[PDB]
Length: 50
Length: 50
Image (cartoon, rainbow over the protein chains, first blue to last red):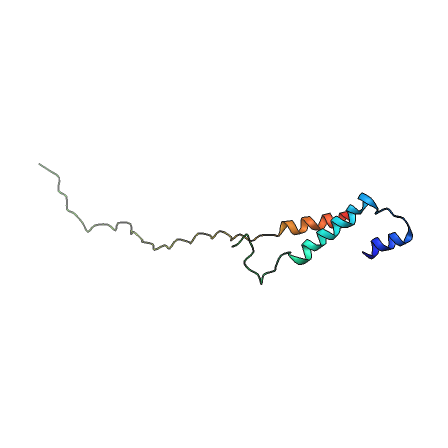
């Protein structure tokens, strides 16, 4: 968010309108990895083994 | 009239030697370990989108 904010403060205004799709998609991809993700050997019942 | 023939002590026949053999046990199929393929797929996209 700081990177997007820094560019906005500088006055580029490139993320206005559809350009914003780049930050938006990235923030979604990061969310998928940190919240669900996958467990290690301690969580033996990974979907393919069960 | 016939020729005489006296049977001597029998000559030694070739000795038979038995053998006890226990078969090897077949190999066991490696159980199905599985990689979290989707996780690394999202990764190269996020680093690429940056």
